[PDB]
Length: 152
Ligand code: MNR
Ligand SMILES: O=N[O-]
Image (cartoon, rainbow, N blue to C red; front, side):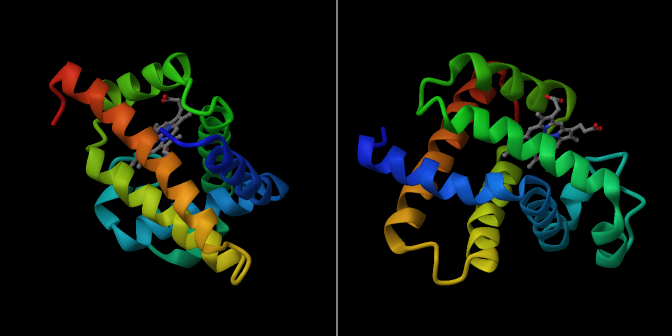
């Protein structure tokens, strides 16, 4: 798992996200969609977004970004003790939304990129290591539930 020190880093980094949850959420989703257009096809409500300008202009996309990062923040603040929080998400993403685990790798990478982009020189090597571990833990625990369901 993560050490106490590592969790403290993760939640310190998370402070940056919480100052502007919508802005971070928006940029994370745009990074995902532009980098991996197939991901956009999983969202009936974002399929109409034909350009980054349109994405940037979408208030509903920002709204969804807030929902997303709020959920992730809840999970992170449990410091690995997140079974109750993670289970329903694993299940809706496998069974309803059909999100391959690869897309969760994509969005994890997007979060790391966005943190650097918004906080250049202020997301240090130790912070990136800790945040990376936390996101891998999240991914890995979801993947365990995906395996249970035989999804993908
Ligand atoms: C590639 C696409 C997908 C990725 C990656 C992804 C990654 C993540 C992610 C990782 C950090 C978190 C946290 C996350 C959290 C959520 N997510 Mn998700 N999610 N996610 C969807 C696609 C994806 N998610 C879709 C599609 C919906 C339904 C949206 C709608 O039509 O209103 C949804 C909905 C949701 C909801 C609403 C409740 C529900 O349906 O369970 C939350 C919360
Ligand atoms: O964008 N993930 O729901």
